[PDB]
Amino acid sequence: SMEQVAMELRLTELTRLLRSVLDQLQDKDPARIFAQPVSLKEVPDYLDHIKHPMDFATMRKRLEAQGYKNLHEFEEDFDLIIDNCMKYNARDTVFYRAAVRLRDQGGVVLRQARREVDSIG
């Protein structure tokens, strides 16, 4: 149908905007601490601690399959990155501290993303 096509165009455009959001958030991780999944070879107990692992490469795979329907779903995954790190790692670690900085800096980006998603529809 024409409606299904229009809906698909909307999803494609959301995917365009979320790709720009993702790039901007990932720039706030210049150490690449959150770039890839925590390695289960190197942290073999990880899934005993963290039930829903997340990282920027995993988000990018989902994004490119158009697997985020709305900004809320995208934000859920970004918050997992931060929140998983802040539980597994102690406060006095470079990992925890990176997550705090990513959260604080990402907030700005996500605030305007929400306005754009609502504005453009």
Image: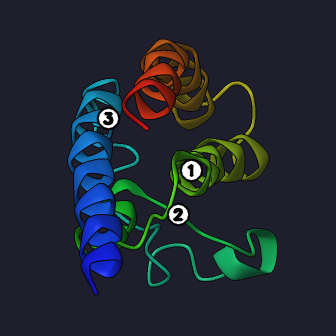
Which numbered disc, 3 or 2, marks the residue closer to the eye? 3
Q: Secondary structure at mark 1?
A: helix
Q: Position of residue 39 (x, y in %)?
A: 43, 74
Q: Residue at x 45, y 16 (%)?
A: 112
Residue type at mark 3? Val
Q: Secondary structure at mark 2?
A: loop
- Residue 81 left/right relative to 36: right
Q: CA distance from mark 3 to mark 2?
A: 17 Å
Disc 3 or 2, which lies upstream in sequence? Answer: 3
Whether residue 70 is visible: yes
Q: Are marks 3 and 2 in contact (CB under 8 Å)?
A: no
Category of crowding for the residue at label 2, using alpha-carbon neighbours closer than 10 angstroms: few (below 14), some (14–19), many (at least 20): many
Compare residues 99 and 2 and report the one nearer the observer: 2
The C terminus, quarter of image: top left
Residue corresponding to mark 1: 81
Q: Are marks 3 and 1 in contact (CB under 8 Å)?
A: no
> For residue 1, what is the image quadrant?
bottom left
Q: Are marks 1 and 2 in contact (CB under 8 Å)?
A: yes
Disc 1 or 2, which lies upstream in sequence? Answer: 2
Q: Which mark is residue 44?
A: none
- Residue 100 left/right relative to 40: right
Residue corresponding to mark 3: 21
Whether residue 63 is visible: no
Q: Residue at x 38, y 43 (%)?
A: 33
- Residue 16 left/right relative to 38: left
Q: Position of residue 32 (x, y in %)?
A: 28, 41
Residue type at mark 2? Met
Which numbered disc, 3 or 1, marks the residue closer to the eye? 3
Q: Which mark is residue 54?
A: 2
Q: Residue at x 57, y 25 (%)?
A: 103
Give the vertical position of 70 relative to 100 (above or below).
Answer: below
Compare residues 22 and 35 and report the one nearer the observer: 22
